[PDB]
Amino acid sequence: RTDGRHIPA
Amino acid sequence: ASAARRKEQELERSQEQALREKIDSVLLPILGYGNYTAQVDIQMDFSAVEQTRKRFDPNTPATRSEYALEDYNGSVRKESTRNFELDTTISHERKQTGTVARQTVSVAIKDRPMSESEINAIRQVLIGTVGFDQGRGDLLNVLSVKFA
Amino acid sequence: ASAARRKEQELERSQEQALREKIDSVLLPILGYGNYTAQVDIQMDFSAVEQTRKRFDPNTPATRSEYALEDYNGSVRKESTRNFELDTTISHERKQTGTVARQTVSVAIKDRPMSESEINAIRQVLIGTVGFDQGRGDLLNVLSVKFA
Amino acid sequence: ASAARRKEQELERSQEQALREKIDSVLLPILGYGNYTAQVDIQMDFSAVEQTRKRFDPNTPATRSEYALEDYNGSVRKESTRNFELDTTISHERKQTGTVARQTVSVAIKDRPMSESEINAIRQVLIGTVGFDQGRGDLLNVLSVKFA
Amino acid sequence: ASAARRKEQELERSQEQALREKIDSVLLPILGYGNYTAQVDIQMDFSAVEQTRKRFDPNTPATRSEYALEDYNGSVRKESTRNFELDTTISHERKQTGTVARQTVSVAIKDRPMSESEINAIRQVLIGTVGFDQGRGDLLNVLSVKFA
Amino acid sequence: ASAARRKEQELERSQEQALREKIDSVLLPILGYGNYTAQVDIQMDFSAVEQTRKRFDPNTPATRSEYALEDYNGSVRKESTRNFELDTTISHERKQTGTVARQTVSVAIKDRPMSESEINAIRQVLIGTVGFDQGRGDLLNVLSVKFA
Amino acid sequence: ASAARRKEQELERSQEQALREKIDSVLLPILGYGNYTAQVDIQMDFSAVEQTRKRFDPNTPATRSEYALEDYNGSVRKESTRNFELDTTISHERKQTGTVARQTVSVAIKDRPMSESEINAIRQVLIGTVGFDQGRGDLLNVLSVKFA
Amino acid sequence: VDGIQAEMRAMMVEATN
């Protein structure tokens, strides 16, 4: 939900 | 650019002259006319530093999104995904070109010598008369010599 | 740009002259004409700092959307997904170029010496006459010397 | 921009002059002509702060849509999905450039000394005459000295 | 913009002058001519705040659409889906630039001293003469001093 | 915009003058010429509030369409779908810019003192003469002082 | 470019002449006319250094996103993925072309010899008269020789 | 260079906010 990251809703 | 270097030399000499004028304005009443001599050396850097700093705050993150799977059976699976937001400071600094990097002042007082107490008092007046900055590497010598 | 550096030197000298004028305006009535001497050194930074800060509030999040699966059987599976909204402050600051980074003032009082109480009283008047700021690194010397 | 810095110096000097005028207007009747001396130092910041704040209210959410599945058998599955609406404040502030960051005032009263009660009364009048603000870092010295 | 800052200083001085005029208009009959002195300091903020607030009402939702499945067998499955409508207030405020952030007034009354009752009565008249607002941080000093 | 601020100051001063005129028109017959003094402070807000409210009525819904399945066997399945229509009020308000946020009035009556009953009667007349509004934070002081 | 080299030689000679002038201005009162001789060698580098530095801060990383899987059974699997944000400073410096890389000064004093104490005192005055910098590789010789 | 340009873009983001 942010920049290069994870948390793919 | 050599003309620029010439004008940099002119700037340094002008600074030295101004400091000498201040030294005279302080010491002429205190000591008198012709009872002292003083010279000033000023070294000035003319670099072109230009810095950009991007700083974060590791110890105060703010969770934006979060996933947490925790199943049991024995078997214990603990999956987790987390996205953070951090304090971000971005500072762009551009230093001034000509800065006094080191300053040297020497003062010689005509004998008839001078006591240590008055020498230190004159040194204290000069510290503040010139803006003595030891942390910058500046140097201030006050001596009592025999004029011919 | 060297013309700009010259005008920066002019600014510093003007500040020093103004502070000297204030020192005279205070000490001339108190001490008299020719019973004191004082000189002022003012060092001014001319950087071009320009900062951008983006700050969050980790301890007060607000849940925007939320999913929570919690099934049992034994087996205990606790899935969870959460999205947050956070307090966001974005401040863009641009510092003024020329700022007094350090100030040095020295005052010498003609003897006939001066008592410690009156020296400290003069120092107290100067603190406020000049705007003494020790946290900035400023320095204020007041001495009683023998004028020639 | 150095012309802008010059005019900033002019602004600071004008503020100091105005405060000195007010000090005179208060003390000239009370003390008399030539029985006091006072000088004022005003330091003014000229930054260009410009802040944007986006604040939420975590403790009062309003549910917009909601799904809730809760089946039993033993097996107990509790699925849930929830969307929220939150109080949102968005404030954009732009500070004024030149602000008095610190103010220093020193007043010296001619002896024949002054009692502590009257010194404190004069200090109380000045507090309000000048707008003393200790939380800003301002400083106010009132001394009784011997004029020459 | 420095011209704007100059005119802001002019505004502050004009406000101070007006308050001084009102103080005179009140105290000149009561005390007399030359039996009092008063000075006023007014500090005015010139920020550019501009706020947008979006507020909801969590405790009074209105159901727009609704689905509810509830089957039994033992097995008990309770599915539910719900959509809500909420009270929505959207207020856009734009504060006035120059606002009096703090006000300081000091009044000194010539002795021959003044009793506490009359000092408090004068203070009560001034409260309302000037618009004293303690919650704003304003300060009002009334003293009885010895005029020279 | 500073011209706008100047005219706002003019508006405030005009309001104060009008209120003073009304105070005189009431008290000059009652008390006489020169037997009283009164000053008025009026603080006016000049914000630019602009609000939009969307309100519903949760407790009186009207069903638009409806589905209801209810089968038995034991097994009991109760499916249901429902759509609602709700009372919807949408009000857009735009407040007037300059509004009197606080009003302070002080009146001092010359002695030869005044009895409490007549002081309260004068206060009652002023309440209505000025439009006293305590809920707004207004303040009204009536004192009996000794004119010099 | 050979004309540029010629003007560089001119700059070096001008610097040497200025230092000689300062040496004379200090020693002519102290020693007298014709009782000393001094010469100065100044070596100046005219490189064109231009440096760009990109520095990080390894010891204060800030986690941006994070994944962590940790399941058990025995079997223990610990997967992990992590992304970091680091403090980043990017400084571009451009050194001034002509800089004094080494300075050599020698002074010879006419005999009728000079005592060691006065020789060291003259050396102390020169240190500060010229701006002696041993860390730069500078050299300062003071000798007492027999003039013919 | 690239980092300085990124800093300038961040300052522009500040101004827009």
Image (cartoon, coloured by chain):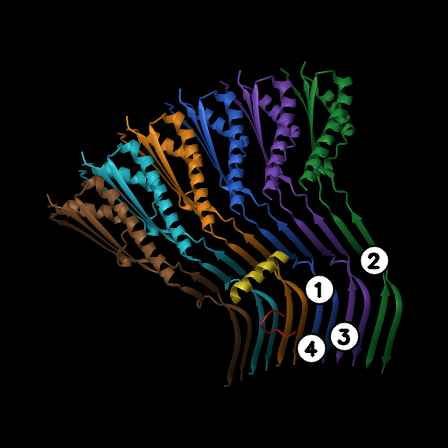
Chain colours: A red, B cyan, C orange, D blue, E purple, F green, G brown, H yellow
Q: Is residue D66 above or below residue F73?
A: above
| In front: label 3 or label 1 | 1
Asked if labels 1 and 3 touch by Cβ distance under 8 angstroms, the answer is: no
In the foreground, C15 or B120 = C15
Dot 2 falls on a residue whose secondary structure is loop
In the foreground, F81 or F51 = F51
Q: Is residue B43 above or below residue B69?
A: above
- Name the kind of residue labelled 1 in the image: Phe
| In front: label 1 or label 4 | 1
Left-right relation of F106 to B71: right
Left-right relation of E39 to G108: right
Please tell me which residue is depicted at 41% across the width and 33% down the height of the picture: C23
How far, Cα to Cα, is label 3 from label 4? 11 Å
Chain of the residue under the numbered disc 4 shown in the image: D
How far, Cα to Cα, is label 3 from label 2? 26 Å
Asked if labels 2 and 3 touch by Cβ distance under 8 angstroms, the answer is: no
Left-right relation of H14 to D81: left
Query: Circle 4 sits on which residue?
Result: D77
Asked if labels 2 and 4 touch by Cβ distance under 8 angstroms, the answer is: no
- Name the kind of residue labelled 4 in the image: Arg
How far, Cα to Cα, is label 4 from label 2? 34 Å
Query: Circle 1 sits on which residue?
Result: D84
- Name the kind of residue labelled 3 in the image: Glu
Please tell me which residue is depicted at 46% across the width and 42% down the height of the picture: C11
How far, Cα to Cα, is label 2 from label 1? 20 Å
Measured from the top left, where is residue G124 in percent x and y? 22, 47
Dot 4 falls on a residue whose secondary structure is strand
Do the residues at discs 2 and 1 belong to one chain? no
Measured from the top left, where is residue D142 in percent x and y? 44, 30
Query: Circle 3 sits on which residue?
Result: E79
